[PDB]
Image: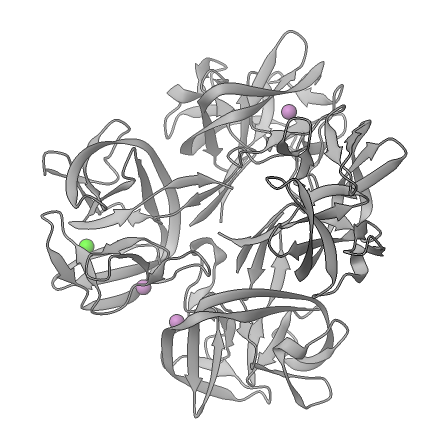
Amino acid sequence: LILNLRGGAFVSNTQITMADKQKKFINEIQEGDLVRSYSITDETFQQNAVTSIVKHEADQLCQINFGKQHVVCTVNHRFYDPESKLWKSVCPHPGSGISFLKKYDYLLSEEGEKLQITEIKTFTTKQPVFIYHIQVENNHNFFANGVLAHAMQVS
Amino acid sequence: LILNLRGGAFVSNTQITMADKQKKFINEIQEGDLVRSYSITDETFQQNAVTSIVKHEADQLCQINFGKQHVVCTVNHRFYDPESKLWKSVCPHPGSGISFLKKYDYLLSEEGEKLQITEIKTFTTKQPVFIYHIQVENNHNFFANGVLAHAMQVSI
Amino acid sequence: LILNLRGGAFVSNTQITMADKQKKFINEIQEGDLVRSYSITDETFQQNAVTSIVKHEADQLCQINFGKQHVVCTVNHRFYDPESKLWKSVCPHPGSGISFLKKYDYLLSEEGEKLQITEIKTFTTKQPVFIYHIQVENNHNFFANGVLAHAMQVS
Amino acid sequence: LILNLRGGAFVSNTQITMADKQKKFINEIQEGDLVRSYSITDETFQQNAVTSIVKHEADQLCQINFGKQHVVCTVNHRFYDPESKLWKSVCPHPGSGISFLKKYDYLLSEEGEKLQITEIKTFTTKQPVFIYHIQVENNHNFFANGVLAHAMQVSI
Ligand SMILES: [Ca+2]
Ligand SMILES: [Hg+2]
Ligand SMILES: [Hg+2]
Ligand SMILES: [Hg+2]
Ligand SMILES: [Hg+2]
């Protein structure tokens, strides 16, 4: 079949925050682990279940800074700008309804606080490195290094 | 990230032949597990390691009967026919270079026998069911219910 | 840009039922042309313009017989079965929520009759033939050799 | 059925360089029209027929300036950088083998000169606009507002 790992994939060293606000590296996540998610509409946090993990590799990645704290993923990531109230990407697929993510846009923290993007750069690796896409039921999002990231595998 | 699973996917029940010819359900297989692979060009068997497992859901499936034996997978699969010397799918995507898999075509067993397909059926579930795709390192193939299948995770 | 042509493509000598009631070979269809379409919802016939025509190649085709007439197309077509009230393909994509088209299933005639599928055959050409995908406005369906086929390009 | 438009698509008023060095708006190009092309290995200009035009729509677009002149396209374009000798994209797919396109990278003019990229913007539009992918035989490339662009209609 054809899968759309939409919201992209994160490097092994990326930290996912649990329902108990603890942190584990995405490559140590397992089916049924309970992670901190966010209802956009109801404007409230809530625990949800990891259904699926997909492991790929890539040599071409994207670093986003939001203060001293950063995150490394594919260019087809999806993050929430709570000030803009839009899902955004550096590289959105034509006809997804996702806005362009830019330098000095906002991300939503795992404490629901607005964080300002300080820098956005491309990043190649000498050889390919592992990347991970996790699916979360109902909310379909989580917190990668403490900011709200959407993730869904479809088709 | 748009990921093409080339071999399609198999129901959780599907038996995988391990390097040492023991059987393991595909929903038990873990990264690093050593599976009975096959070098097509060389016509020689080989042990190889699983690097990736992908789980998705489907309620539209395909049952290939080859005598009394059978395998249940997605309709876009890739089984090797050792008579025609071709990888075959019941439902090839246009201009993919995969031939139609038809009634009375041949599959390759884990021993290296030619096994004849006696029936191809559609199978529908009233609930979506879990399906599994395994990436094998070098030869990117394995024995599903005793017959040779290709599988590959490819980025687009 | 990745473009899913929902409804597949038809060979050159496939007959399209025009607005003007006459038949026309799909390889002659031009943008603006008005074809006979159907509203499944309204259960009435309508005239709609062709907004887009994709042309491609293939050597692997699907023949569907209904009475003493047939249609030739890619295996990932989409036809309406009026008996079941479902869109069907011989080869549906798992995710698509499309049902299997089978022997003795029904198609909808351009005059709203239920015609029985007598034979479905998968065949090859010695070298590729041109296949055509036509998008139709608002209804997104037309009549191929007198039976109702869906077609819609999306990203 | 599933069709990858490798090379993205251009806005209707984008200019295509014809074989005789005349210009035509891409939204007027027709099957059999002759366009200017480049062989990278031969490092010479060829003339080729357009075999296929695919028309879609988009609200997310990309503008690339090379001095006074610009080109507007989808973010999954492919332009030849003749300085680094690589096909490039603002937004390449993780496994495509395509480098990133950035400020102060180069493009190849329809007369064979390096043209420096001076600006890359990404802009939403409020209503979707028409966009056009064209298939050129043999070289699968053409000149879009005077710079070398790749385009190919491939099944998955
Ligand atoms: Ca069984
Ligand atoms: Hg980036
Ligand atoms: Hg089948
Ligand atoms: Hg068929
Ligand atoms: Hg851009």
